[PDB]
Image (cartoon, rainbow over all chains, first blue to last red):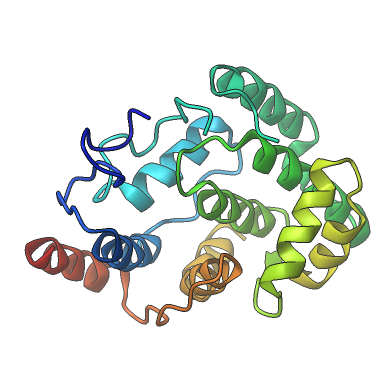
Length: 181
Length: 49
């Protein structure tokens, strides 16, 4: 695992912290403040923009921030991430980034695109965070808005687990509460 | 709508980030700072490690 320091079970990091608890704390704090500076970004958005989001979030913690995952650690084998992520994003473009859809269709397509990017798992760390920012922003460009406020941890996971298996029903139910306006 | 969209982003993004992080099981304080205030705080946190 080339992301780790040679001797240890800790991720190589720009603050050179060698304790697990401390690195986690500083990463939560610094990501939190970086998120508070991320701008909405363009309507036209692909893999580059997702990467851009992850660079901004993690630039203080990791020298590889904004780069696609380089090990396998269901999730896409690392060397195919760019190919399938560009394919996925080309398709989103063809549907005009979901802009102009009635609620129920929007929910249905958001669930689909969330599930596919999630399974792709494009970053070594921070995929879910960068992902949800990308769709918060996409939703706003399409006339909608996302709120994750009411959602139990265990339901979110289960719903992503069955989505990766081809049943998007629980992720759809979650998204019809998360989407509004 | 492009300025309406950006302003809606700015007003929700931190609330989102807190609730998105709580999805993965971690409760952090809400960030109430503006971008420029948060940029200054980042340089302070870098000094502290």
